[PDB]
Length: 179
Length: 180
Ligand SMILES: Nc1nc(=O)c2ncn([C@@H]3O[C@@H]4COP(=O)(O)O[C@H]5[C@@H](O)[C@H](n6cnc7c(N)ncnc76)O[C@@H]5COP(=O)(O)O[C@@H]3[C@@H]4O)c2[nH]1
Image 1 (tube, rainbow over the protein chains, first blue to last red):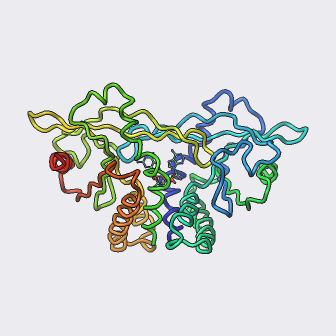
Image 2: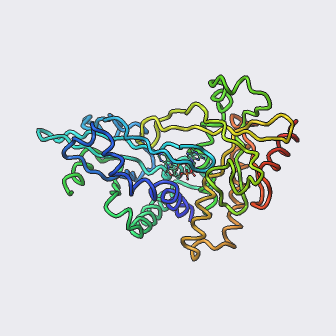
Image 3: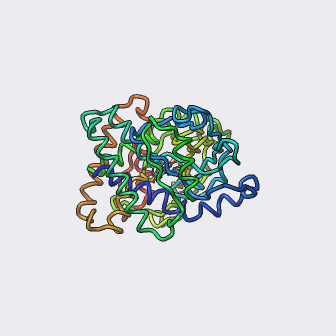
């Protein structure tokens, strides 16, 4: 129930209007446009623990330092909720693929998940650590259900679920190859 | 409870770190500090319908067109969810009081409410308009409880509840004047 609202908010307040124009947005940067092996879809990071380092380069998920920040994308300006020209931008990362050419992709954590974690820590009485795990599952399936119902979001995103024990670089490299 | 999550997200993902220094953020702009009748607190707009025009100046809520966009504040930069330096800024508005001196304040709609509205329209089976009305109340009470439990957020915000039939300019002028 609570995860349901977070999934809808994640769509209506973000994904619905940032995914259809994600490809077009990236092309505005020469540094990004001239790039090969750059998948033009949002890789939504969904860790099972619901916690992450807001900074991915050299994060705990990236032990070998194969992931590197390539600068943000052109910020999308949109007026919403009385706030003029609110900024919607994404971070481009560089993933070393051994001796091969490095990979480039947009990586973002599912921000509603941070609410679930913070709730479990700040108010364990409303959301227990056990209850938190259940809502993550609901969130994923609900979000997937919503996005699958949006033709404009078709092939504009990739849900990357992984446990925090996994090497983010390894997990990412597989999905990057599978494209 | 869906409204509970929306309230917590509105806090943890926004209000918790934008409210305590909201005043200081405003002072960074020369045009704003020297301004009189300028309350340095976020007036969170909470319409009962949960729907609004994203542009308040000359909006449907502002018939007499007394509200005017006076520019945004210096954006607060913070890296969140793998996104480097997300921008968190607010819009300053000017409210005309007839021939008298105008008022200045930050006005924002409660963005989680738009989710409640959109849910009621897209999937009425999951969230009916009757259930939506109940969830707005829960959201409001929850949001108040959360903010009241944070002294850093004390007296740095103002919840402005109103029906979409009322004149936003009037309601705001009332709230601003009653706070002396
Ligand atoms: N008025 C206003 N100005 C803001 O800057 C702002 N930032 C957040 N919020 C509201 O706080 C709550 C929690 O924030 P969160 O990041 O976890 O979820 C966000 C986040 O997952 C995603 N999103 C929205 N804007 C951005 C953005 N600029 N960058 C990345 N992700 C974003 O979409 C969700 C819903 O956004 P909103 O529908 O605008 O309202 C949010 C939300 O209800 C804001 N409200």
